[PDB]
Length: 102
Image (tube, rainbow, N blue to C red; front, side):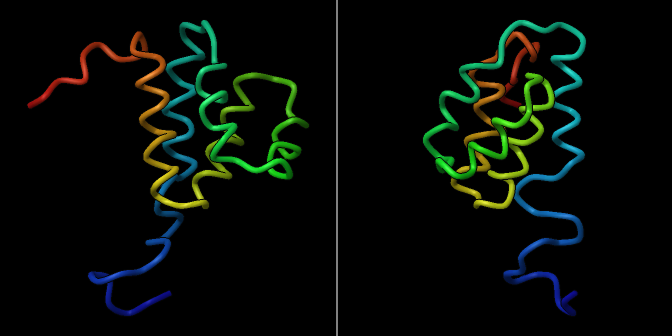
């Protein structure tokens, strides 16, 4: 690791932009009341690459597919990560009961 967490360091412990923990919180909302997960991929399809889609194409399930989308973007960067975590809420507002302002 690194001795001096404060300035700029990649991966604090088990990730940075996106972790497996957050990936579960997302599916947890769909596992209860499913509906659709296309708009989430249709928007990420651009940020992702043709070769990357192959890794996700292997997954037939929809729920599991979302888990892969986070694994790729989670390592890509923050510019795409913020879009993914936000897209899930921006595309599926029903999942939340009011983003609230403060």
